[PDB]
Structures are given as structure tokens and as C-alpha cells.
Image: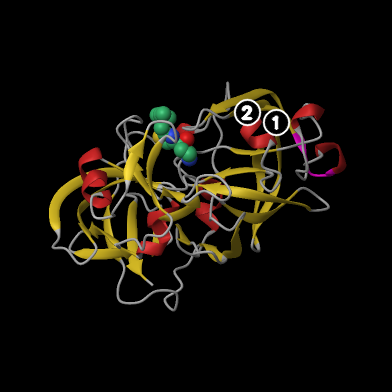
Amino acid sequence: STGSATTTPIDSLDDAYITPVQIGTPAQTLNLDFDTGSSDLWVFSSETTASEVDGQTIYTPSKSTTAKLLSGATWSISYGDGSSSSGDVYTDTVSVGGLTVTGQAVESAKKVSSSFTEDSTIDGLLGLAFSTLNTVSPTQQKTFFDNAKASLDSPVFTADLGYHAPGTYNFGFIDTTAYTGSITYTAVSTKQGFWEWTSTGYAVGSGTFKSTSIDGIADTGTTLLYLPATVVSAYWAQVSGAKSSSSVGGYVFPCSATLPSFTFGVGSARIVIPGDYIDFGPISTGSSSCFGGIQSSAGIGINIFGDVALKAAFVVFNGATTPTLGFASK
Ligand SMILES: C#CCN(C)Cc1nc(C2(O)CCNCC2)cs1
């Protein structure tokens, strides 16, 4: 089997991407944030605290003839931004772009933190990291990808995120028309449950390439590119007036600036992030200070190749017995 679904930015900044997901019988379509940095499929639901729902579409298991309560199973998760959610668990039929998994654990939120309530466009998350990170207790549950793997034509999914434009998640096949050149595959460590890999270095703008190992995770659920402070300082030093602002919480730059590109290494290959992809717009409406898309990872403990990096590439999440990551230019 295969599946293919379009993913769409939630706003003009590409803060996150939503993909329609069919849950239950008859189908209830929710727009979920596909997150390769976590491993829970959770949704706003009829059980979510009413004061914590503000415009989201909810999953109602009582209206699904295929829903079954997963008795005694609960879940509780926290993300890098301090957001959180928790609730009960059902199993139900879940379809993405024509690919159907029966008996998928669908984690129904009883509580969500404020950042989820405030984002009326995201109805939940669909985790695509390794199932060892799934938070369901006492019986840990498999991700949608893990459950689908045996049925897929090939045990892979691909992320082709757009720049201020829709893109595509494909399951079970590699669309050889979607990228230029070849896909360079690189080793993955699953020891922390992430799609964790090692970039071979970087360049800023037209500068020469600096060969250096940068361990990090491929995370479609993180907006920005978080890299070591040395690398990030070398990037922003090329932008007149750029500086790290403790009040804003990161590097800012004059909105009048045109930004240099940023290149990261994948083996001997190179992915070039155009400078415009690094511009996240005014810090507040009307401000002439703009927020940078490359930020320091020093406070988080891990480097994150988030959407800023991944949207410059066609990215293969290869879930073969020895998982690997592939990157192609596009
Ligand atoms: C701060 C800090 C330390 N870590 C929690 C930082 C991290 N946060 C994550 C994510 O939550 C980011 C969003 N997508 C899912 C994974 C992975 S590592």
C-alpha cells in the first residue's frame, strides 16, 4: 500500500504545517501536525476541557462505530516549547492520503496547554518518531508509520515541505520526480527515539564549506533550525545589525536586510537553504526588527533540523530494519 497527503502551512510564516487525517467510521477529518520529533497521535476531542478548545475540530469517539476504548491507557506528553497535553486512549481506523491503519491508538486529549488552545488551526499531532518515545501507559503504543510499515510497498515516508506553499507527505514510496539530483542517505541513531543523524558541516552564503560534525534530529514539528552557538554566531555575523536579544529570546535582524543562504552537509552532498527561508518576519506587527530562522541550540541540549532546514530538501525517513535518513535538493 501507499498514501499521499498534502501538507499546508498554518500561516504566512510557515510556523507549522497541517495535514488532513481521517479518523473513525464515518470519517472525522482533523488537521494534524505531523511531527517527526515525537511519537504520539493525539487529538482535540469531545473529552477535551471545554474552556481549552477554541475553534479546533474535535474527534468524537462515541460517533465512530470502529472506536474502542483502550481500557486503562492514559497518555501525557510535553514538548520542547513547554506545551503539554494528556488524556485517555481509543483505538480506531486512521487514514492518511488513502493509506489506512486499523486499530491505531488515537490519544484523546482531556487537557491541553495554552499554546495548543490558542492555535485554532491545529487539531492535534501525528507523531512519526520511533515508537519507543510513545507516552501511552501502561502499554506503549505504535505510531501510525510503525503500524503501517508491514503493509507499505516500502517501509518509508517522505517529507516535502513547501516554502510559503503546500507540500506533501508520502508513505510507502519515493516520488522520483519530486527532487533534483540524487538522494544522499545518512546513518540514523535511534538511541534517543529520534531521527538523529550527523551533518558533515556548513557554509554561510557564498563562503567556503566548514567540515565539522553536527549531530541533530530531523524534526518536522519544530519551526526553526537550532544549531550550536558557534555556527549560529558565524551566520548572523554576516547580517548587518543582527544580534541576539535576550528580551526577544533569540537572534533578530533588521527587516530591511536580505539574508545570506545557509548550507548544511549530508555526507558529501550539500543542501542550500535560501536566505529568504531564514526570515520569520517582524517580532511584532509593524516592528522593523525581524526574527531569525536560525537560532542557538545551546539552551536545549540537542540540535534540531526543523522546518527551516527540511523545507529546503526532499527528505526520506527510511524505516528499514536499519533506519536511515535521505536528503535531496529540490
Ligand atoms: C528544552 C528542552 C529539551 N528538549 C525537550 C528539547 C526537545 N524538544 C523536542 C520536541 O518536543 C520539539 C517539537 N517536536 C517534537 C520534539 C525534541 S528534543
Q: Tell me the residue at 31%/49% (across/down).
A: 241
SS category of the residue bearing label 1:
strand
Q: Nearer the viewer, residue 315 or 256?
A: 256
Q: Are marks 1 and 2 in contact (CB under 8 Å)?
A: yes
Q: Tell me the residue at 59%/60% (across/down).
A: 7
Upstream in sequence: badge 1 or badge 2: 2
In the rendered image, residue 236 lying in the magenta stretch gets the answer no
Q: Amino acid at mark 2?
A: Ser
Give the labeled residue for mark 1. 109
SS category of the residue bearing label 2:
strand
Q: Nearer the viewer, residue 45 or 61?
A: 45
Kindly indicate the quadrant of the structure image that contains residue 196.
top left
Residue 112 vs residue 169: left or right?
right
The answer to whether residue 69 shows anywhere in this view is yes
Q: Tell me the residue at 34%/29% (across/down).
A: 299
State the mark number for residue 210. Answer: none
**Few, some or many C-alpha atoms within 10 Å of disc 2 (few <14, some 14-19, many ≥20)?**
many
The secondary structure that dominates the magenta segment is: loop
Q: Position of residue 77 (x, y in %)?
A: 55, 28
Above/below status of 274 relative to 68: below
Give the labeled residue for mark 2. 85
Q: Amino acid at mark 1?
A: Ala
| Magenta-colored span | 64-68
